[PDB]
Image 1 (cartoon, rainbow, N blue to C red):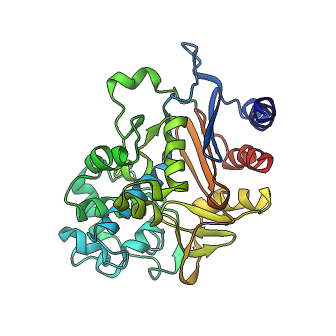
Image 2: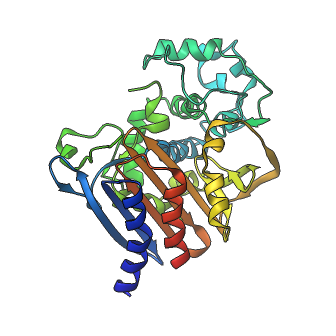
Length: 349
């Protein structure tokens, strides 16, 4: 059984690490309440430090699930509603087009064509960020087109933080990470933990909200286990995780939630790859809005990809099978390949 599971995970990982020249990769699996770790290759090629389940990786956009969890907590505390106008939570935006844009539109990339990235002219400076949003004008009606945007979910996280009266980074570190039991999860890696921080193989406005998290395979599986069993947490945090398990609209095979993206399970590998493809990141898509928000549970795969320069992360879980998976690597390798690994493991289980 130990031999079967290792053969399954090796067969999924080893060829893809080889073909994508990935130095280091950490797998964490939650199987009917039991964790299993598979660690491959090197956290650093230069000093020969090996990947373990405690190695810290950059998870890029997977950070948006943490961001969605903080928002879920502000919703649970009645500090904000998803149908609030964005300018409600930041006076500097009153008079701007954010008077006409909901928190939901920001969270789900439908505010009306906020771009993939802040322009280069916008530096990590609160005043530059304020002025960017004040002058911004939509290309099309809010609620109509999905365009993947860091400025969009960045503003969602920043405003959720404003609704709670504290800076985003403080809330994440002081409240969110402790409430989820996560001591190896960081927006700002302590000097003491730097030896665990993997090297990547190849500081922005609202980077914390969009791309900020560094974590280990073991900590990210703790978060997936929380997502699989919100009822085991204290009630405010149970409610915060459930708010990330609500679907608002569909693009193709994908139902958009807060942070999480959902598919019917089973589904072909090719359709899971197409949901996670470059056109989904880079092009606008007309949404099919659902009659009412749908519970993202049962026969479904919830997933998120995330990348920085040097790093490539993937997380997926199947609520109705108590099945969870984490794949962290120190190369930004194609999403199609991350999903290839994940699908072989989830198929094999």
